[PDB]
Image 1: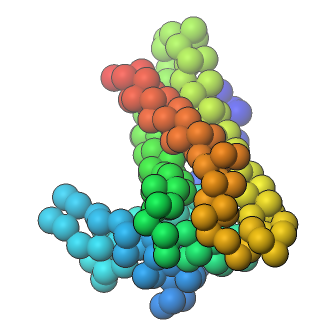
Image 2: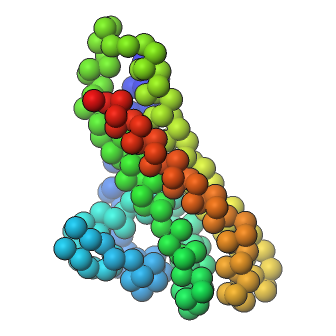
Length: 201
């Protein structure tokens, strides 16, 4: 149960730091790429608008990559190459479940702190407190894996002049090597929440 507190203090501060960061107006290369492709709803604008709910939704993508601006630049570079080719627009969709992932992590954590008082009770089931911590970690872990994957991608997508140049193949590369991984990671994230969300109630 202290691990849980260590966790909350640890990630919830890391996010304070992340929120203070200002976006650069350019939205990191991604204004007219990822954030024009995608349409945030409720009740609908593009993800690049002034509209509040989207500016939050841009942060969450940045925070997915722990706001390492270099990575976000280096991913834009790639996304920008993929956005010329409709054939590879679905790859661009998979790359932005980093957002969905993150939202759930903020939400799980928002509730953790809330419900933290209830599972403090010496009375609360120890064989379920365990279930919860396990999920909690798994969330925090997926997060890691994701950033990990994004970087790894960035390395192999610029490993050869041909993979910097030919979009047809760049995308193949990514579909081949990472799309599944980004799919499943996006799923694991839902479903851990949903399970967790149950557990809180």
